[PDB]
Length: 96
DNA sequence: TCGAGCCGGAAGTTCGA
DNA sequence: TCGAACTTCCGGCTCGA
Image 1 (cartoon, rainbow, N blue to C red):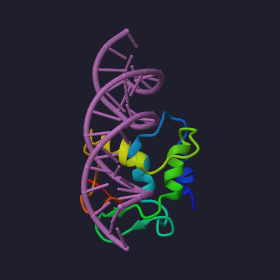
Image 2: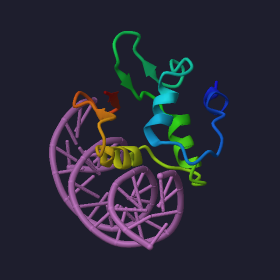
Image 3: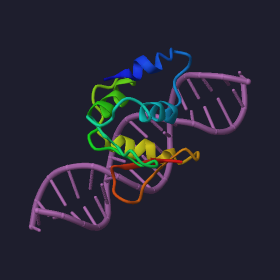
């Protein structure tokens, strides 16, 4: 249930691109047991990023990273038109 | 009445060409 | 060698039960 490293298998061919990784993990395995992926147009909410949130901080050899970070670094990520957060709730994320 | 998560700004080091 | 890129630290705002 972690086909990320198996799907990616994308080697140390340079650090991955932030959103490309997140976007690759998005349209990936089930995502029903650890998060919520609607089966309609393109809506993505983070229900329980327990494995995602700790993988995010693990890549940096950092043991634990709360989710506030993503609301932090992901927010400042409005540099390119790639992932915009939804003004609906707070754990609702979206991509263009 | 009380706690929790989200956001605002800046600085610092490294990548590919 | 050049410029941009993503990360992390400090402290502050408001909502629901």
